[PDB]
Length: 252
Ligand SMILES: *C[C@@]1(O)C[C@@H](C(=O)O)C[C@@H](O)[C@@H]1O
Image (cartoon, rainbow, N blue to C red; front, side, top):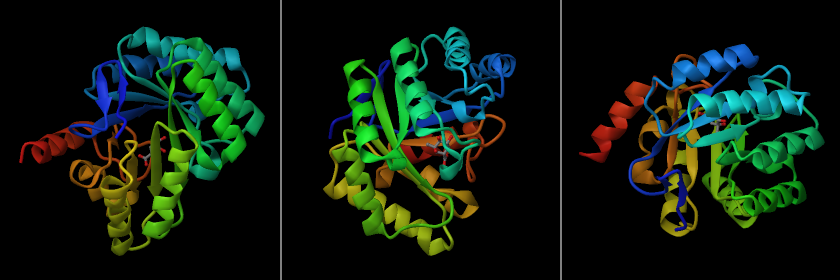
């Protein structure tokens, strides 16, 4: 295992780390949300850039990043544009997606970026290498909002992310049955037992999948998302309740 340490937070050891997502449409709402979020307890702040309406302007995006970092100078900060294809709020070109992520990297404001695997292997690998050349970690991600692949498919998808240089592979999948929740836990455990080179983040979405957001320590999901006021994906619970459960499991 190669853990990821960001600002003295060690991802891939101990209790799963709690991530919350800040969603603001404009600079004013990003400011307001940052001030509210800094009164919540969590480990990693994700900025969901795809909720920001002035996405065409790299400088407006960088201004909003500055607002967040000013509000929370010491927080691990994850910059994520989630494409509509993968459950996000809007669609941009691959070129502009890469431009925004490279700008985030260059700014020095962000600790990690999210890169979607299915952007394309060559673009992903180049962007991973760019991030690493500038001391930024990559959460490489995939989201299926319709269904759950087989455990074997999910393992191979996470292993491919490892192979492309992901620091932290991530998969979120939609259960169509309770069995699919167990499939996601089975894939997660297979990574822990047999492919434990990098921390992985996994989740089964929606209400049926909630247990997967709680059982990260035993089966091997290195982080979990909670909601401050609004969920950033189906199935997230209130962040204080998430924290309570994680602590109970860690100390059981
Ligand atoms: C990583 C990610 O896609 C996971 C979502 C989830 O299922 O909890 C929340 C998103 O905000 C995040 O980008």
